[PDB]
Image: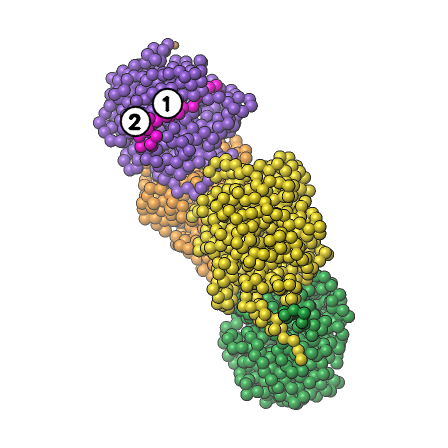
Chain colours: A purple, B orange, C yellow, D green
Amino acid sequence: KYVKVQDFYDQLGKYVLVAPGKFSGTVAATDLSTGWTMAWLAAWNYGDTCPIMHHMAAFPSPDPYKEFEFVVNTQGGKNLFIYGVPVTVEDPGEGMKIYRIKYDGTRMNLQRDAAEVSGLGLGVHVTITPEADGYAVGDGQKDICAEFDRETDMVRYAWAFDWDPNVKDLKRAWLDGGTMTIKRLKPTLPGGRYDLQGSKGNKIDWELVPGGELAIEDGKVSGDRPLHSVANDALVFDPRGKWAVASMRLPGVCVVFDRENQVPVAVLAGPKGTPSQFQLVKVDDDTWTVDIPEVISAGHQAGFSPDGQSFLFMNSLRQNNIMVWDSSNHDDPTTWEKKAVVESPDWRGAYPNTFHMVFTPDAKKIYVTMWWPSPTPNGIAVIDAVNWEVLKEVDLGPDMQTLAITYDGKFVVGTLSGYQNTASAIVVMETETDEVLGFLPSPMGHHDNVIVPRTLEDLRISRSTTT
Amino acid sequence: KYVKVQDFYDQLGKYVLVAPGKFSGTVAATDLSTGWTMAWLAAWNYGDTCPIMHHMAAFPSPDPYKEFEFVVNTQGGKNLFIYGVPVTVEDPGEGMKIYRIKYDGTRMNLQRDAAEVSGLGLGVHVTITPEADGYAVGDGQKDICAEFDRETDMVRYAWAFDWDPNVKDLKRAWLDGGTMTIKRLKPTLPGGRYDLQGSKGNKIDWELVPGGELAIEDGKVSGDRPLHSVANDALVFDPRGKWAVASMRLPGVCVVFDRENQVPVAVLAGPKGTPSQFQLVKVDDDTWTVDIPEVISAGHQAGFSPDGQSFLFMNSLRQNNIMVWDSSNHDDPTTWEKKAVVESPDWRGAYPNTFHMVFTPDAKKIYVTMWWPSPTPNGIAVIDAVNWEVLKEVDLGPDMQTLAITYDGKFVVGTLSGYQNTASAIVVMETETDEVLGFLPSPMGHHDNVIVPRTLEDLRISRSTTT
Amino acid sequence: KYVKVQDFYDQLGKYVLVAPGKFSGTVAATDLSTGWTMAWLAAWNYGDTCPIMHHMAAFPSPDPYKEFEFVVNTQGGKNLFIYGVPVTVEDPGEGMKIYRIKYDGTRMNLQRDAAEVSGLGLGVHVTITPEADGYAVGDGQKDICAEFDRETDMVRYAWAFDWDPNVKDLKRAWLDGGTMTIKRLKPTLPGGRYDLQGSKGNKIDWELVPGGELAIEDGKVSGDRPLHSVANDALVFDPRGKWAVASMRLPGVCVVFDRENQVPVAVLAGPKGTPSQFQLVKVDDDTWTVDIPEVISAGHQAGFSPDGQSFLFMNSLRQNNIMVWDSSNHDDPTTWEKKAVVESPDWRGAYPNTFHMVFTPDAKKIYVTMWWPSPTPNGIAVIDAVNWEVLKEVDLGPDMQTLAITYDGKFVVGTLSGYQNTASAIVVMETETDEVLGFLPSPMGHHDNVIVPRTLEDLRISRSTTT
Amino acid sequence: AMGKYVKVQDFYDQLGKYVLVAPGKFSGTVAATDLSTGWTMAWLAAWNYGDTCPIMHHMAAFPSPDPYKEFEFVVNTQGGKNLFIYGVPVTVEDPGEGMKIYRIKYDGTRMNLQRDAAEVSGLGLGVHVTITPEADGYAVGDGQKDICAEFDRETDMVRYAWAFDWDPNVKDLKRAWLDGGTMTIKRLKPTLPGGRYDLQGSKGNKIDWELVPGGELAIEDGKVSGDRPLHSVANDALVFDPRGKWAVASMRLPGVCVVFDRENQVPVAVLAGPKGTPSQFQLVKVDDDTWTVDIPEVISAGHQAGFSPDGQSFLFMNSLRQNNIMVWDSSNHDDPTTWEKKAVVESPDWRGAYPNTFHMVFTPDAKKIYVTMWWPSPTPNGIAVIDAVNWEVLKEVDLGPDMQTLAITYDGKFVVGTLSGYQNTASAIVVMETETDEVLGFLPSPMGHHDNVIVPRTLEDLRISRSTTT
Ligand SMILES: [Cu+2]
Ligand SMILES: [Cu+2]
Ligand SMILES: [Cu+2]
Ligand SMILES: [Cu+2]
Ligand SMILES: [Cu+2]
Ligand SMILES: [Cu+2]
Ligand SMILES: [Cu+2]
Ligand SMILES: [Cu+2]
Ligand SMILES: [Cu+2]
């Protein structure tokens, strides 16, 4: 006579979803096998005066119901002013915190701020190393990314990026090309600490929004040094170890780094029509440069397939496609060559933009997000990652954000976030026949979510290899 | 072959759930027909520096999906420090704000703080008048309750309560009895405004916890004037009009007020073994007293059946039962006589604490929360409200809080709130055979929830007649 | 046969005196041409529960007998406890109100509380802008000053000051030097309002008394943050426009601000033996610092001559003198250099404390208060403002407070205030030979007084350029 | 002079070494001024002592051998709806109830609040305050509760208290006084332990404010709220015969005064106010605590009541339906039942309620009287000078708004009065010399005074202070 919602959860498995809430100031872990929120944390309870809880990633735990740890960062300053909400805090906290939090099988415990430990505050993507011995954060206001040790929260290595435009006019500063400098970033305070917490280091006063390359070009992004911006987004990891890849939105390139030797080794060229790579040039032991003759399109999402055989970078806005390299040679990234471009008429406009992805465990399919400004329906596209073609797209609702998959490959679980002021939900889609199974309440503005991994292998399709 | 959670929502009807989040700092509306959150709001975005979003009530709307209005208040000061969250905020806000918020079919819009408009801040139960033309708020730190005008947010009347113990020793201050003064409260400021915002008027530094009557007695509740406390809880309304009833936890009584004439008219005596009523004595045109020879037990929950034939007050300290009056004579509340007591051998002093309830539309059943401190499972009792007997007790999880019902009477929708740091959820129970259908995620600390009513008749079983 | 007092008033001219009354809780306007009080207002009539009516300034009116407007603020909290009056109020109001009052040719009319309109409550000196289009208030419990718009009572700009002492011990916190931060203070509530009414923001629980820097250093001033105090006193105006100057008692400096561009531009070093200026350092677009090696003396009175050519700051603790700068270069205050110091063998350490002044219209002479604790006769010093020397000292009575001048420059009109409990009067002195013409009754504890100006030029010797 | 400027000191030098004291009504303050220098000597603000309705009302000062070294005085307060009847748009909707009787000492430096005598005795009273001619006590009356009492100076306990009640021939507010009735005079005894009354604050109030000038029209018209307005007589003051023995209670509504024997604690006579009535009405004894007086009809209310300084004349002003000064020969000190009307001071300028003549002061030799002429805004108020040998008006002088009380320096040279702005406009102290009645001018006074005194030095000084008249 009555439907029990427990029948829906029994099919999902014993998986734990975790998501931060952006303007909500909260972070929450949910039991997909019962529908309970397991625990939640509100950063204002800890004196955080701008708790835009932003990106996150969770370390593997063999039983997340018993305990797991995760990293979540924050944004501050004028990031508070760029969504639809008529906020009244004219002088908010500066954000760029890197919180370490541990779920202990009952509650969330705020452990520390790694930005205070290390001295380095970064406010965009968080990823976990494939060894689960560490994590990385990037930032597109300071243009710095770093890998941190898990035990000590100290930086292992940090890199700063800078743009030298051929034309010092914001309208032409990326389109007409320039030179990007890659600089080893070194500590300046006692104990190998950085002096780069909060707003210290910012070139621009907020992270560029979707299609925000147009806004910076039009002089509509405030900041000390926008002509010098490259808008670093993430540092993602080859699941085979050894390499990490830093993505640069404005110049449309990814930089491959040697994690052990602490040097860049390769520059992958995003836009369709460019060669596989641009030439990396060493200037001294701490300085490299790369010349980009013109920037045809900005790009954003970057990541590896879970077997490390493919590396993807999405061009967004001026071109909308998925660029794919053969990354099968683990010994030498300067050999990685463009093998395919995924294109579709689900992509003729400036929008949708595809900022997030997740692969199935066997690397044969990809789930990618399709974002538009209100009011166009946002949704998910399914990719055949064998033939590099779009299989399907599904409409869902407003402001599609991030995606995760259960580690058996059976269910994609994503977040929609209301542009911080309208409808928000968790979405579940089954991957056997790619149908939407429904939505669960989620009163948060998630710009990230994960399913807590159980093993190092699970990390390959979590917040480690892709964002 | 897969289960679609949409099949679960299709059965619930086109109902909107709204709930505040306590320590989350947020309030959210959820579409029970789709599982989407419709909109949420985070009060820190509006400069609220202690956004403990506390109680709330929603005005009827002929279509809640197009728009609706609601009222939600806040607590502050040392309320922040009495839960299991190791808060680190140094100088928290004083709370006692009374926000007016409107959903416009897309987003929540903050209208204003009524405590600023009126001058009167109050931080405990919020209820809507049966005419939907106003609302009331009670407070047990200041011991004041008031009815406010919906359009102007100005006070219609306000009453202040004081205790004068027979024995001036906290251990004996209520046990050995005393006199309660009931005092008309009038404004002092230009434009008819009160001077009672934030902590102004506070006798004690936090709202008494469940069983917290023992703490104040033991000298463990700080404040200027704890010997004078009565811990007013709510001002609930007779669904037939005319009368409002103010609940006083510490002296174990309820005061019936004439809403039109602005006078108290009756004092209902909570504990088993006391008469139906105590004698109200007029001292002057603004001042009444009531002599209580001994307080046998504190009380808490207070409410009317939806036809107003019965009035309930829960004893919840030294006794644990539901006291029931015959309130069928609408003309004269001094005639209201005790008619039944609901008892169970399961119930035992302070716990379960039965501090929330909702009736079915036909007044035949009641759903009552059963609250315990961790780790005893909390749950819901089902009460036969014709014979006055417990039908069924169901266990659910930690920290059972409020209960609402769909207006067709088919589903009870409640919240569990993890004591602000562990598991939290929305629960759904069908009322035909009283079975739990399951849980939906809710990463919030709700001490209230409503389903948005459509008509004045719907208010009879919403946040107007009971809390 | 008999003397008429009319012969005394006839000589004074058609001028209106206005004064607040401190502990009297009143404010009054007096017709110096007839001896009548024109109108008085008692703030307890308007629900003020701590009506310490403190500082005030009047806008120009072409005919003050037809109408004029003025601003008067209040103090509260523990300021009620620091004077000789054995007060018995236990819950005093917090003060920091900023009342707008209009005299309409018959009565005073309370228009509004500007601290409620703007959200910013401040309780020390009030001054009018030289354009008479706004006013400013400073506060030395919160260390905030701001300029407000006359029409809207909204803040144009507000500055918050903080002390970071070299030595974390109240005894040496100022003597051994430290760094002062100057921070742009921005609103946090809907409609651009601050959340800083009443005691919100107080670092210390009363305004420092004369010589009261010794008390804070001796740990005898209670409050949350006395190590961080700078005791801001006033925001006074260059009569030539553009610049406003905030005085800071504890670190002995004045900060010059650009009103239009809303930045600080210079720090003036008070004590004899220090350079003309300390170095202003920009930290970011909202924040500046200034390093002070040692604080040789506290300062207090600050103001411009009426032609803007001289700027004065009194040293008033460990030195007792008037420090004078050449402010003739209106374009660049960083060029303002010390040019004179007024000294006297009779002036050593704290007393006489010289905390009020008024110039003659031709700027050649200054009248300055000589204040002492009871029982030493207090009086007025006459200063030669061309040679920078004391001309004359005249003893009057107990507790000399403020000084005003008729705008023809003929009569200085001052108040004496009995330390709030003994003899009080208005004093009149003629400026040709600097003789006391006598006293008029004044049952009030005035810490301020003004003659209502008629023109912008009159403001130059009213409560605009000096306090 | 040695310079061209006028010094204000020459003005004060003529006045002598006298101290003016006044309360401030809505200002919530009281102040003492040195007329010889122009300084305020000391002032006190009742809000500093936690008073939540400091309408500082009437006052009287005990004699001091040197008031510059010390003097003591009594000042009372009003509260409740008295806060709502002036021009000020007050916002305190539930103020304190007032009816405090404060004892204050000026100790040569500062005012010290000694205590509230209403709390001591238990009896709170809000209208006129007077000093006994022996300076061993004081009295207060009140027109909301209709009670008067004499209190001991040393203990602040009540020596005797009387309650007055009206029983109208018609229980219709329009006619309750016009058509007559019976006034009861009742001995009030303490009802609490320790000889205390239970009559502080609003306890005992029949009406919710003191009747304003011409306010008898308002109570008649049902515009004055309260529990028992039909029972009102509006007692105003208890004034003293300077010869001792007798005190006189004035009753506004029924237009009579009651003469009391102070030592034996009984009423002895009832003087009938209005022109055309007998000298007296018949006092009837009912029992040892209770007397009645029959008043066939009330031709007019009255108000100011007082003795000349030699005790030979008693005066009662009629003040609504008639406007005159009624004068009795009170030269027989042994028997007030023999006091008979001897004169009536009238003027073609005095018709109906205005000018209302509610305050007076005699010169020390009793030859002249200075009387207030009060009008509502905007008619100029002033002072009438009365020849008290021929019982005629000598002179009228216009001054300003809201003329209130009058005192005189004890050498008889200068009358010092207050004007009080109706609590919201212009206020001042006024000085008039008594040889030629020339107004010498005004001094600032930012207060709403409904009283003022010069501090007396001797018992003989009290004869022309707040003892014999109000
Ligand atoms: Cu990204
Ligand atoms: Cu390899
Ligand atoms: Cu984001
Ligand atoms: Cu409750
Ligand atoms: Cu609660
Ligand atoms: Cu100052
Ligand atoms: Cu002051
Ligand atoms: Cu009178
Ligand atoms: Cu009066």
Q: Secondary structure beneath disc 1?
A: strand
**A83 or A202: nearer the viewer:** A202
Residue at the spot 25% in from the left edge and 25% down from the top edge: A392
What subunit carries mark 2? A
> x and y percent of residue A302 in the render?
34, 22
Q: Please tell me the numbered disc located at residue B89.
A: none
> x and y percent of residue D297 in the render?
56, 85
**B239 or C333: nearer the viewer:** C333
Which residue occupies the extreme right position in the image?
D65
Q: Secondary structure beneath disc 2?
A: loop
What subunit carries mark 1? A
> x and y percent of residue C414 in the render?
62, 61
Relative height, residue A407 to residue D304 (above, below): above
Please determine if labels 2 and 1 lie on a single subunit. Answer: yes
Q: Please tell me the numbered disc located at residue A180.
A: 1
Amino acid type assigned to the residue bearing label 2 in the image: Asp
Relative height, residue A167 to residue A454 (above, below): below
> x and y percent of residue B198 in the render?
52, 48
Is residue A163 a member of the stretch shown in magenta? Answer: yes
Instruction: Tell me the quadrant of the picture where the N terminus of chain A can be found.
Output: top left
Amino acid type assigned to the residue bearing label 1 in the image: Met
Which residue occupies the extreme front position in the image?
C387
Residue at the spot 29% in from the left edge and 24% down from the top edge: A294
Q: Residues within 10 Å of mark 2 (few under 14, many from 20)?
A: some
Q: Give the CA distance from mark 2 to mark 1.
A: 13 Å
Q: Residues within 10 Å of mark 1 (few under 14, many from 20)?
A: many
**B420 or C343: nearer the viewer:** C343
Is residue C164 a member of the stretch shown in magenta? Answer: no
Q: Is residue B137 visible?
A: no
Query: Dot 2 corresponds to which residue?
Result: A176
Residue at the spot 40% in from the left edge and 38% down from the top edge: A81
The region drawn magenta spans: A155-175
